Each structure stands twice: as C-alpha cells, then as structure tokens.
Length: 138
Length: 137
Image 1 (cartoon, one colour):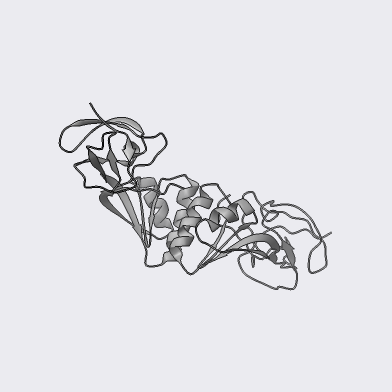
Image 2 (cartoon, each protein chain N blue to C red):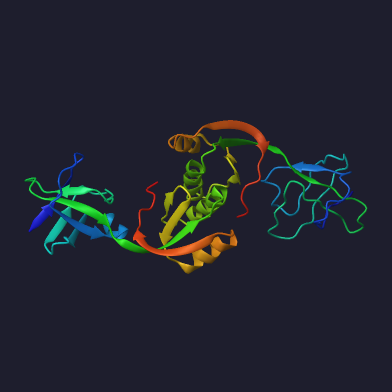
C-alpha cells in the first residue's frame, strides 16, 4: 500500500494523480482512491496548504503524484468593476467566509443568503461546479 | 437647552454646524458643542448614523445644524492595481476593521500593525488627517 508523504516544490512527473476538495486539502493525512489508480494514504505536517499543481512525493521518490482541486459547489461573482468587488470582499471577510479572489472574479461555497447580500450591491451571482482555491487564511 | 431631534430628509439652509468624529456620529443621545460655542444635546432616533452633510434640526424648526465629519488620524491605502485593493479589503474585514472604501482608495484609523500587514500584500500606506467615513454594512 503506497502512502504519500513529503510535498516538493519542483513539479516532477505528473504520471500519478489525485483530486480533492479544499475541505480535505487541509487534513495533512488521510486516504481515498486516487487518479493514477493506485490508492494511497497521506503524511503531511500540520497547517499545510495544498494547491492545485502542488506535487507530492514519498521517501523513495519513485512517484510524484499531483494534487488537483476538485470541482465544488460554489457561488461565482464576475464584474469588471473593482470597487463593487472590493466592497463585497470586505463584507464576506467580515463574516469569515472562505473566499477565492481573482481579478474580476470571486468564489465562495454556495450560500443563497450570501448571494442575496451580494445582489444587494448590484452584483451578478451565478452558480458553478468549479475548483475552490480560497485565500490563504485558516 | 437646545435639542436637535430630527434629520430632515429635505435639505434647508444651515444656521450652524458641529464637527464630530465617527465614534460620536454613531451616538444618538449625547451632549455636543456647536462650532459657534453653544451647547446642544443630540436626541435623534436611536440607532442612526450621522454622516457629513446631515442637517439636524429642532422641533420648532428654528435651528438647522450641519454635521461635518471631524478630521481623523487615518492610514490611506492606494495601488494602481485595483485587484490588489480587494484582497486588502477581505483581510481588513476579517479583523472587523472599520473601513472607508472608495474607488482606488482605502481609509482606516491609523494602526501600525495593519500598515505592515498591508505592505506585505505590497501596498504603499500613507498618512492623512481626513474625515473618516467607514462602511455601514
């Protein structure tokens, strides 16, 4: 039974693979079927951030699996007006809502109350099944 | 004494004014000093936010006091890259920091800890003595 351990920075062979949510990419240690086929456990230190593209490796180095942010039910906000988005970011952080931030776009786990709070800013909120990479801050 | 009890939606020619910082402007019941030296007691409806430009009057409609946001010690954050400002807003709100948000310009009570924290994000912080008007949520 192969078990993942250390996390390298160097993006080696993408021959192996695994796809997990944000929920599990902060467990440091767990197990479920993978993408390369070969099931495997986990051995990562405390308080680690696993990002889409972040390669992993074992003690032997024979394998270099890759972590992939699985699609997750999220609310997506797209606007080309930084101000309207800035305001939003403020109020979401004020409720400690894990949020993904990119130019012209925001992502947070689907929640209608939040969608209505954002629509109250004249923002368009649409549902999506996409990878969720919220801001570093657990 | 003199009591200001209403905030007329309808403007009017001001007969006086009182300068006040945000902490006071959130206070419904309080004794203040008009800029002409007279003492007036604010007795407006509870839970109301006084903004600069607000005009308070009395029952008899014989006094129209204009609220002026007092100059406060604030840090000012800018960046030609608007996307950089957003992340700062998210973190500031995470810490529940009163914040004034304008297009390409943030403002908050000067605090050196927050300043460094924002420089990390690579934001240039500046200082000013300006009227502070934080978001109300």
